Image (cartoon, rainbow, N blue to C red):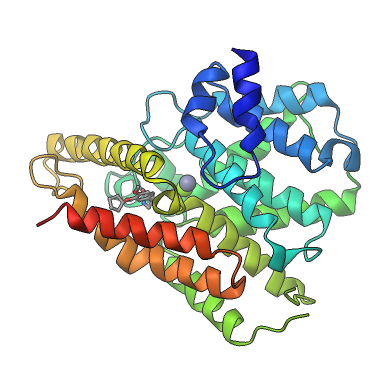
Length: 321
Ligand SMILES: COc1ccc([C@H]2CNC(=O)C2)cc1OC1CCCC1
Ligand SMILES: [Mg+2]
Ligand SMILES: [Zn+2]
């Protein structure tokens, strides 16, 4: 079983990694093994003097805080976003662009980006006067929570993976991670995309030229947001599994709403839903506009990813008539 897991992990640098198989082969530890593999591949343990035992202790602890009974926003999704970010970071157009600390920040942010997710949306938490919404004043409720949990867990016994970073490095990484995870709030999508389009239009090359730090964090924010919204760009057998999972989570939220006498949110009514039309709409209005813009920034590095997205859109559309 360990040999079979080792075989699947050879594809860690490839779009379309069999992440569900890795989750099963690792004994429900996809986040831990994928993060460990990526840290080794990028030589991050040596660069930041991270003890291996500390890294594993932190990762297992973090993974434990993803909920086992939430269909989509679980440790498998975290592992997938981590691995997807890892691939985007290695795009030829961005070679030598980011510092080792910026790379560490992006991968760490991806790992913690949805930790302790309850399987319901920010709007649901707000509308139900939840403890989380009261704590966070209705603003990036989940995302603020994911960050607080991810950082707080570093303080557990033998969990501080940043113990050998300088004070300056820890301060910088903390700010970058906060800026990145907050950008995963799906209410910020339109502003994030508008800013990304402006960067494409004012692009300078010779490899992308991002001498300014404010431009670099903006690229990392969009990168992680792309990874978060990468399901429809993956091979169809993976994409369909992600669709099944998000719909299960949405339908469960709708059951909670219906039990409370609340109006059922869009796409959350199992008795009145069109999964296929909803995926086509999701791609057309959100995912394709985002990915076409990313592809333009790194042209032509992401062409195969965009082609797959387009093929998947056509497939889902073809099932409707
Ligand atoms: C695989 O699909 C999806 C994958 C990811 C998301 C993110 C944005 N909202 C979330 O809760 C997470 C939505 C999806 O589809 C939604 C729109 C159509 C139905 C669900
Ligand atoms: Mg999220
Ligand atoms: Zn996510």
